[PDB]
Image (cartoon, rainbow, N blue to C red; front, side):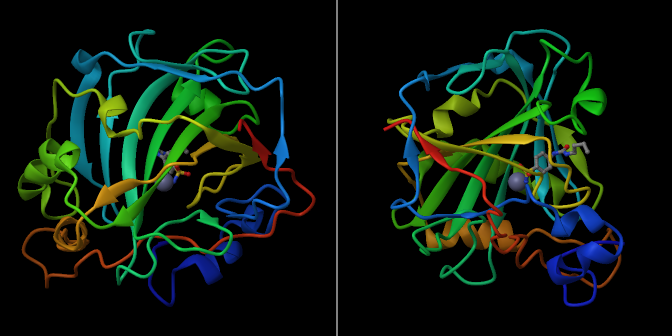
Length: 257
Ligand SMILES: CCCCNC(=O)Nc1ccc(S(N)(=O)=O)cc1
Ligand SMILES: [Zn+2]
């Protein structure tokens, strides 16, 4: 029912999901002149076990790489959190051209793509389904992806896409530690926000990395060559899946640096 095209896209999500016009919507434009350094923010701690990697899924608007989330083998701690957050997925957002494709922007600058590494609060809640609609339920690391040199750390992910070309296809995706995709510096911004597509729950604590990672023009093309249609139908490439930035509405973006 929802998507990224003209009739079902971001500027229309509010008809089915009124929280779209809420006070804690994501993504945002990070204005570095308006951020507040917070001395209480601890370094980000990620410890992921590659044996938790499970499956890669074509979800029609994007692709998801899911992780086993039955225990604390793969966790996020530190930064603004007192609780341990359990890794459950990573995915990307991209745009129709290299000029845009990130969700977050920094001082108005649009990057070519963005990596999301998503976690849920296993200290307070017993499942992702319980966590997902709670204010303290989710934590997502965002990494801005700057077009330039090919990023070899994306190879396993890109190589997998040929097995999940059309909507609904899934394949095993094992023995992968997504902390390998993160930049060298985990200096970050944090703010309270939302999922960036339906159901748009205001349940996400965002961790946005200061440092970008690279991606090539041709790697982005591989994302855009995934198909949003089911097998046998007319091919409809996944040209874009980035939401525009949303108003801060009085929220503070904190910097660790
Ligand atoms: C409603 C239960 C959660 C559903 N979502 C998921 O399974 N994945 C997911 C979707 C979007 C985001 S984002 N773009 O980081 O705001 C993070 C995770
Ligand atoms: Zn996302």
